[PDB]
Length: 161
Length: 47
Ligand SMILES: O=c1cc(-c2ccc(Br)cc2)oc2ccccc12
Ligand SMILES: [Zn+2]
Image (cartoon, rainbow over all chains, first blue to last red; front, side, top):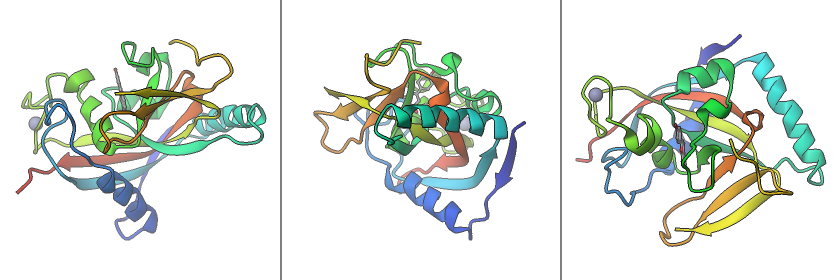
């Protein structure tokens, strides 16, 4: 049931999503090893992901969380980068999309920094980089990230390096 | 997939060394996220 609707670059929704992407780039401690060396992106396309069943699944859980947390879903917009991006948009997030070895246990990980999610686009550690050139810092190949609506509810705070 | 710590719905990883880093978050049920925008891009070589 998924359809993708292109946003025009003139559209203010395009512009605000692009600004969140660009403005949350930072330098990483691997010096670019996983995700490449860059200070900004060339944005080629932004598309709205529409799937009624997946949206209703999300809003249903959101309501449950909110009723467990004094009517506060604690909803954020966050980035996700994944080799499985094409299955996520058609079938939704599930346990197949979890970072089993992540530092907070087996769950599905999201970032405020777009450049952190960019490190997982070709796999954990950036995998072997782009399929065409095997280059984790490929400047040619087109990458995709998700900008996702995420219900955190009552979040457990873990201080960490 | 693991479970949220008892009484919580997610985990927040607060950056605690690198003062430039923003937070990262984990959810333990797929239904707590909706993939709203698909962004196609290239990273750009610094000049
Ligand atoms: O965007 C993310 C994707 C993933 C991710 C995606 C797929 C797989 Br397999 C493993 C990790 O991990 C992250 C870890 C911290 C912050 C963000 C991310
Ligand atoms: Zn390439």
